[PDB]
């Protein structure tokens, strides 16, 4: 079978903690009354939620109410425990309250309000400095949750709220997040297609916090190169082919050999053979103002087949790309 793997950082943070911290199944959830909140308008509608802007009628403050479509009860409890554990963390969305509507009995999570700037509007107004500043802000959130023994597992532009006027960033949507336990086999059907690490695509279940670092690398490539998404797969099998077209097929085989991964028979038939491309080949007239040798070196140390070889969030924070900022 496959060779075991563990995170290079915060490996045993949950092992040395009591049951209370990570056993979300035994966590007691106390649901308040939604009558303190008046729903104002719909902000977004996710995979299994309806997000509304709301007013807390007890203090006239704006909040956000995420109304959960009652899926597996264990999943709601997992998201609550993680948000409660990370509450107050740098650039982490703050869970202010947990409520239930008296008549519907539907569960709902109450969050601090974020005045989100449009992805297309932000994409056309960001400078080299803005990208470095916001990348550093995301790194603070990731180093923090990883230190708290949690992997986000759905890192992407849509899960990062930015109030550009106030230069305020929040990592949201902790519904796929999970407690890291060294040597544990996790579900590989996590993260959004374009952001899936090669470990998920090759069905390597013993992954860690390093999955988040790959996703972060995909977001950085899309920003500096102005190609969204950067790895544009049409399905999960094709997603690995898009990565292989850039990173090369040689290093993919070295990766599967190192971890003794049993690659699906179908892959050899669609992967083909591809050379490793130089990051500079993605530089053009429309994006050259966002590219620098430091950005390319940083991106290269994030987007690597081998999850263990990828930089950790704290290592990434020390990289020369962040010196100016
Ligand atoms: N704190 C927030 N402030 C503002 N908008 C938010 C906030 N949290 C969520 N949203 C909006 O709601 C959408 C869906 O919420 P999300 O937490 O990502 O749920 P899901 O797991 O269903 O995708 C987001 O993409 C965003 O537009
Ligand atoms: C407002 N939600 C979309 C969005 C847009 C841009 C970024 C982004 C900006 C600079 C560097 C890296 C990513 C992010 Cl995280 C999210
Ligand atoms: Mg989401």
Image (cartoon, rainbow, N blue to C red):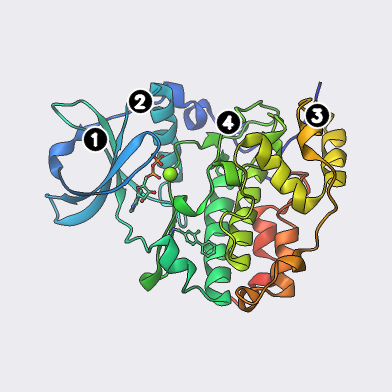
Q: Secondary structure at mark 3?
A: loop
Name the mark on residue 28.
Answer: 2
Q: Which residue is mark 4?
A: 189
Which is closer to the viewer, label 4 or label 2? 4
Point out the image quarter for the C terminus.
bottom right
- Left or right: where does residue 29 sit relative to residue 318? left
Pinpoint residue 166: horizontal percent, then vertical percent: 37, 71
Quadrant of the image for the N terminus?
A: top right
Q: Give the residue number, with chain letter if any, for mark 3.
A: 261
- Mark closest to the chain's N terminus, 1 or 4: 1
| Residue 179 visible | yes
The picture places residue 3, in percent across and down from the top left corner, at 82, 28
Sequence-first disc among 2 and 3: 2
Q: Earlier in the sequence, mark 3 or mark 1?
A: 1
Which quadrant holds residue 204? top right
Residue linked to disc 1? 99
Dot 2 or dot 1: first in sequence order is: 2
* C-alpha gap between disc 1 and disc 4: 29 Å
Judged by depth in the image, the label closer to the viewer, 2 or 1, is: 1
Q: Residues within 10 Å of mark 3 (few under 14, many from 20)?
A: some
State how far apart marks 4 and 3 are (Cα).
17 Å
- Asked if marks 4 and 2 touch (Cβ < 8 Å), the reply is no
In the displayed structure, 266 sits above or below 7; it is above
Residue 89 point in image, percent of width and height: 46, 52
Q: Does 14 sit left or right of 169 as displayed? A: right
Mark in front: 3 vs 1:
3
Q: Quadrant of residue 113?
A: bottom left
Instruction: Determine whether the beta carbon of the residue marked 2 sits less than 8 angstroms from the nearest atom of ligand 1.
Output: no
Q: Position of residue 18 (x, y in %)?
A: 53, 29
- The residue at the point 62 percent across, 55 percent down is 230
């Amino acid at each position: 079978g496959p060779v075991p793997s563990r995170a290079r950082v915060y490996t045993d943070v949950n092992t040395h903690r009591p049951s209370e911290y990570w056993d979300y199944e035994s966590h007691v959830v106390e649901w308040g009354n939604q009558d303190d909140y008046q729903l104002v308008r719909k902000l977004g509608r996710g995979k299994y939620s309806e997000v509304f802007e709301a007013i807390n009628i007890t203090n006239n403050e704006k909040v956000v109410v995420k109304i959960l479509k009652p899926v597996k009860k264990k999943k709601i409890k997992r998201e609550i425990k993680i948000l409660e554990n990370l509450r107050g963390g740098p650039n982490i969305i703050t869970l202010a309250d947990i409520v239930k509507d008296p008549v519907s009995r539907t569960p709902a999570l109450v969050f601090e309000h974020v005045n989100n700037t449009d992805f297309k509007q932000l994409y056309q107004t960001l400078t080299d400095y803005d990208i470095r500043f916001y990348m550093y802000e995301i790194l603070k959130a990731l180093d923090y949750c990883h230190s708290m023994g949690i992997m986000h597992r759905d890192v992407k532009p849509h899960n990062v709220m930015i109030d550009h006027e106030h230069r305020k960033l929040r990592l949201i949507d902790w519904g796929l997040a999970e407690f890291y336990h060294p040597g544990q086999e996790y579900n590989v059907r996590v993260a959004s297609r374009y952001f899936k690490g090669p470990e998920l695509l090759v069905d390597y279940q013993m992954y860690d916090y390093s999955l988040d670092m790959w996703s972060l690398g995909c977001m950085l490539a899309s920003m500096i190169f102005r190609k969204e998404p950067f790895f544009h797969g049409h399905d999960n099998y094709d997603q690995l082919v898009r990565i292989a077209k850039v990173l090369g097929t040689e290093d993919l085989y070295d990766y599967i050999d190192k971890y003794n991964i049993e690659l699906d028979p179908r892959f050899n038939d669609i992967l083909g053979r591809h050379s490793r491309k130089r990051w500079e080949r993605f530089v053009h007239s429309e994006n050259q103002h966002l590219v620098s040798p430091e950005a390319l070196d940083f991106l290269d140390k994030l987007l690597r087949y081998d999850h263990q070889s990828r930089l950790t969030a704290r290592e990434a924070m020390e990289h020369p790309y962040f010196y100016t900022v």
